[PDB]
Structures are given as C-alpha cells and as structure tokens.
Length: 231
Ligand SMILES: [Ca+2]
Image (cartoon, rainbow, N blue to C red; front, side):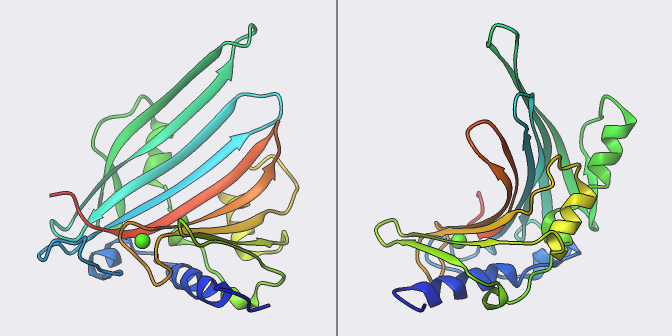
C-alpha cells in the first residue's frame, strides 16, 4: 500500500542499503554524502561507521562488542575505538557493570591499535574486525515482502520492519562472525529521522533483531553516516 510517505520512506532507506558492501574503508575518503548548510564551506565531511553485537540472554550476564570509526575526509585520517561492555548482577541483584574501550586508527584498510592490549587474542579480534558495511549485501528494498512501514511526521521519524529467514545472506554472515545463541530468524529494522530527502542532523541505521522481550535481547546494529566534521 503506497499511502502517505511510504514510497519516500522506502526510497531513502534504499539509498542506505546501496552502500552495502563497501569492502575498502579508504573508499569513504572519496565518497561525498548529502550536504546542507551544517557543513562549513571548506569541510568535506566525516563518515562515521559503527557495528555492534548485543547479546543479553535470559537470566545471564549481558555483553556488547563493537567498534566506531570517524573517517575524516579533511585530514584523510581515521580514528575510533573497539569496546567491550559487560553488565552483570551480583547475587543480591546489585549491578556490576563496566565498559572498556581500546583506541584504534585505520590505515590502508587495516585496523591498528594505538595502545597495546592485555592479550594476543583480543589484539587479533581488533585487527581482524570487519564492519557490517564491509560484508553486508541487500536486495532492493522493494524485493523484501510485507514491510511494516511507520511514520511520525512531527519529529519526523520513520521505520521499515521486515521478517527475514535464516537463509538470508546477511543473517548467515552474522551467524558466521558472531556466536548468536538463538535459532530464531531475525527481523530487519530500518530506522531514520530528520528530512526524508536527507539531512546532516538526521540519522539512518539498521538492526537485525533476533530476540526482543522483557527478559532477553539479542540484536545487531549498524550505521554508516555522513556528518559535518569537528573543527
Ligand atoms: Ca543524515
């Protein structure tokens, strides 16, 4: 059904999905996204890339691992960090939570820690890291069936939700790169806000939701966004 802004919503999301894959992160130095007057004249923009695997099983410790990189096209340098967040409850129900960040830089499509690590295995996990934009690959948005499109014109914000099967290319890639403890086929959720044609201030992201209830949350989030740079 093409009511309201459903077609415009699908169109903007297809523009996000078109970026999958971009195997060489250096390519971002030469990609120009959408520009407004939030970019100061001489600023060429920064590409922020972020992938995170959230695994919070029922009745168990919670853990998230991911990375963020800031690809600055002005300086042609890229810095960010890998992180491991852990949230646990001691026997009295008291939180014992932490998050550790390991600074890194990107050079010649390689991930290089800028501080040493506590062990070799973690060093390799950081060096071998691949953002979802480096191996994801979607079909045209319109090829995904029975989409649930939502639109709040006041923000404005929007979303498109689809049920995927376990034979989906992307799902198979996630199960190979991560130890996801759930047989369930995930939903793909596209989210956006700000002008439908695009904006600097606005956001675009995606998620693969394997489980979502009050006791358990297992999901994967990814975003690739063109933003004004820091001065
Ligand atoms: Ca935007």
